[PDB]
Length: 292
Length: 292
Image (cartoon, each protein chain N blue to C red):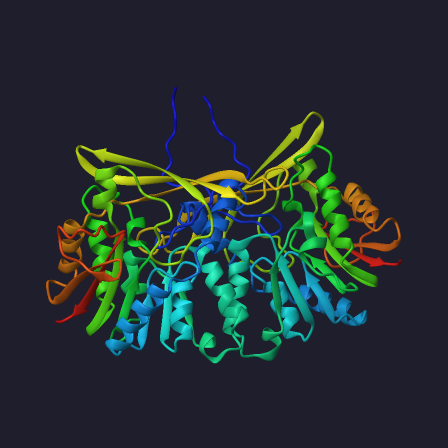
């Protein structure tokens, strides 16, 4: 036959040698990428803090921690936060931050942990619920639909919802895939959350299995500052995929997660959304309120 | 042609989803395996602590941190220690322990950083050197000879040595590859450090290139306690490779890293070594004292 011998198994680490793909060209630009979004937007900060304060939230759970840039702000703003994520490569940056400022009492009380949406109920002790559960940055769209039926989407949505205490809040969002799906393109640097100081080009690939949109793959071509010769920049790339969530479908899913027992409202970008409005938002934000 | 479309780039992470190979069957037995090595050996604790105290060492650098079991020992014993490693998947465990015990004065002062033997001098601020520099556990063997000439072994050995202040010590080991190379079989469960509680079989593969032993691959078949039916255990495997370092060759390599200006002495499983000796050591430990 034609066997294939491997030095070490995929997923195994060894002392003294960098992990498997921690050094590729793609991993390098990606790190530059995830660091280009920390400069929070004034609109964003004002909006989120106002919604939380207007509802008297103190206990909040960030279920899309990432590098922790959203949770750090809350921690600073005085909230009592527990941040979780399923990615270790991203958590690592958050853990680094908590250790550095471990001297500030608020950062000592910051709880960062590992968890999955699919098993959230068993990875995090809900207690009696969290005043507010957040999932911003279009992070829910990272979860693909392997089974064909959005069952996994529902299991995760149900798990996340269950972390909200009655009267509590769930602030979850998604990019406007209605526009991207009909347009076939995802505009670069439109983030309402963090002003990106990195230049990039985006190639959008949409995959339609039978007549159903199944995936939107984005190929980022990041211009890196001084990688060319005489100061000129270089250009490297990486790819990331998302599930194309449309407002109507999503609106249905998130409500079904609350058993219908909830108060739902969707924001345009940060301002109210009304169907047919002249304004085409880049992100749709759903703030739900566990009625029961 | 035949192009291949990937969901996301190799090395890139995404918020809500687990990293690339974090869940493979191999990464799950490997996790269990590295956890089965923490029960330090009284012989090991006694030998290492004595050698350190006897030489009046206080500032120690562990360049093969891993899960930090060697360093945790020193941190507890009162030493001033800084631990580095190039693996993020391993460091993750050391960082976790340091945080869980950050309330104990010693663990708060423990420095855990990322570094690579190849760039050691630029990743770690030597200052005026470390009293002792350790690289135990047969970890140097993890570094392969990619270029054919052991240039990378030499560059990593020179960068490490450079971290040893004059009058300082360097404690680095390697398995008896002489024995393994001749016997073609690496015995399982011969660890002089950390008795193991896990049962496992090992298939040894030696690759000789143009008559020069180039590498040793170990396929571990671990018996997992109760993954079978009625209490019955399961069997899973993973693989890890090493560079077969022979005593004579390594002895010349590690001395030249000090430019000859050193006091070399090799131990065989913590007790002195003399060729032809009836006792076949499982590990060869080299203790070098920086003379110049």
